[PDB]
Image (tube, rainbow, N blue to C red):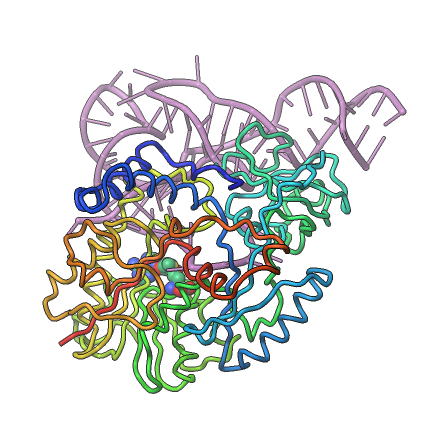
Length: 460
RNA sequence: AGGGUAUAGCUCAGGGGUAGAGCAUUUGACUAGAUCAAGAGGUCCCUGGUUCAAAUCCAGGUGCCCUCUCCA
Ligand SMILES: C[S@@+](CC[C@H](N)C(=O)[O-])C[C@H]1O[C@@H](n2cnc3c(N)ncnc32)[C@H](O)[C@@H]1O
């Protein structure tokens, strides 16, 4: 609709092209079709998901209560507008709020401000512009000025600049709460509000300090993963890559905080964020450690590392290229950087399989779209580890696996791949809201999401 | 079969031989700054290798980073 395709390096886009135009897909669909599919994907990746999805912390508040409180909250934020809050029938603890956009009639002001690409993406998802996000602003900006926020999608704006000839993307208008002086004079690492978005291109609720013990902003497939893993109360679960602990706290909440959830991460501050989240949401069965997942198997003779076959369930939410991220308007990565994940994923996978009890469940999940990080890893896993066996999932929401890794149709039907190019981009407005069938909205929330991949394994 | 990165206070270009920009800061004019000028600035992370010569190329070491909604 409003935004162009995701700005990729020629080599990278050709890499992904090689991915989606393999012999098998061409065979079962034809070049003319697969190419259009790929281009449609690239066109969709630049646009926000049509649904703000919120996970309810059932261990502190029920979905009903939280939904009502959020109804009051949306009443306040949108000055009395009328956007619905659906409840997913399959994901019992997930709420869905439709996105009102895009709005092409926003009049651009002269006082401008430029944020980082990531901050821009956050703004498109319904966030305000907080102080650490601004990397450029009009030198004549005073606190209170109605300014126009632009996203430096290329990340080429040198901080503090008074002008920018690079690539900007209009995100909308907002009331500033700081002058350019207050921001860039001296070096105060100041926090707080910077630009209160009043007329965003996409209208989504701001989830900063609202019900922090009851909510958790989480993409639909991410919330789905913990359900697919299906943790039982009293079991021993471990996710190698956990920070900041969305799926971790979700797993803990599904177990009614009765059991043991060990969460690892390589970076310290991230682990601290895990612990902070767990403490915030009221989960006590969560124990977080700063540790290398690839070296998590006990070898010497003396917390991690852990003995092999000592965990009931294991979640590998492996680090990835993150190509399935939405909205992602540009990606200035090298191809070597994009394909730099398969080995690490395989190491973490091996460490996971070794750490898994017999008849245990291993859920491997990424947020990327590449074959080499998804289906290929499933094939590799099924070959190297013959004790593992691919399992069907519940709930089944996303599409089936992509052809190309040499898996059978029966095998692909047991994978869950979310495709951004599944359904057309819905340009929702209030008139579209009023005349909308509920099943259409639910299908929309299930299909128009970020790129994601879920695979389920069982040991013998 | 993991990868990227380290350069001025901040944000970053560059590049085998005299250290570069924007912003911040400093000073001087014009009416505190939507003006004009002027200069203050860095063992280019550590170590070793290649080389006449490494801030640049290579290897090892270390720190930071590779999202999976919102203080960026
Ligand atoms: C996709 S993110 C985690 C999202 C998280 N699972 C949730 O659902 O919020 C991958 C994480 O992997 C961690 N990580 C990166 N390398 C790792 C490694 N070798 N071992 C363990 N964790 C790693 C990163 O610090 C990052 O927090």
